[PDB]
Image: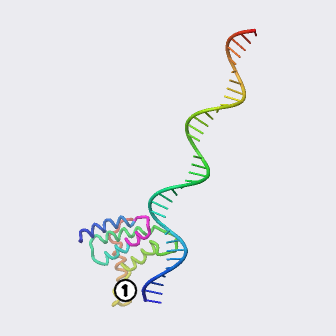
Amino acid sequence: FIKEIHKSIELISNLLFSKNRNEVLESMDFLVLADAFDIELSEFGIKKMLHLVWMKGTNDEGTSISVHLIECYKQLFLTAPDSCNMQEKAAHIAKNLINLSIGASIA
DNA sequence: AAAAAAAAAAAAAAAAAAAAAAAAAAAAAAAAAAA
């Protein structure tokens, strides 16, 4: 089942760049639900979410791709467990933001 | 607080109009021959 889920992550990393809006949105929700667990290649899928910052649209109904990407990365890398103070809230946020740019390419 | 209804968007198939290309017919011009 884990091998088939990894094949699924490999296919959803390609389906992120489709033309339908709801396909991209449910693909992003699937990758967020995978990375809420500790699936190994799921992080790779999250990297291909980062190139969804460019696809813009002035439609103004539902949630767009970038407006959903803000919420996805906010839940992933901009939160901490709520038993923390204000100080280590910012420390965990800054640790996640620093670790987001350690093993990074130019793109 | 949840469910139902209405509106908008998406996908597939079909139809209409315009543009381009092809074919046919008619007319005009030139040259040659005969009385």
Query: Does residue B13 lie above or below A49 as drawn?
Result: above
**Chain hosting mark 1:** A
Residue A33 lies, in percent from the top left, at: 33, 76
The reply to whether the magenta stretch includes residue A33 is no
Colouring method of the image: rainbow
Stretch in magenta? A17-27
Q: Which residue is mark 1?
A: A89
Q: Which residue lies at the image location 31% right of the left edge and 78% below the top edge?
A: A36
Q: Quadrant of residue B31?
A: top right
If the image is split into quadrants, where does the C terminus of chain A sit?
A: bottom left
Most common secondary structure along the magenta stretch? helix
Q: Quadrant of residue A10?
A: bottom left
Residue type at mark 1 is: Lys
Residue A63 lies, in percent from the top left, at: 46, 75
Query: Does residue A68 lie above or below A82 as drawn?
Result: above
Q: Which residue lies at the image location 48% right of the left edge and 75% below the top edge?
A: A62
Q: Which residue lies at the image location 33% right of the left edge and 69% below the top edge?
A: A45
What element does badge 1 sit on? helix
Q: Tag 1: Cα neighbours inside 10 Å, few (<14), some, or many (≥20)?
A: some
Q: Which residue lies at the image location 41% right of the left edge and 72% below the top edge?
A: A25
Q: Quadrant of residue A22?
A: bottom left
If the image is split into quadrants, where does the N terminus of chain A sit?
A: bottom left
Residue B18 lies, in percent from the top left, at: 61, 50
- Give the total of numbered labels: 1
Can residue A5 be seen here? The reply is yes
Q: Nearer the viewer, residue A37 or A44?
A: A37
Can residue A58 be seen here? The reply is no
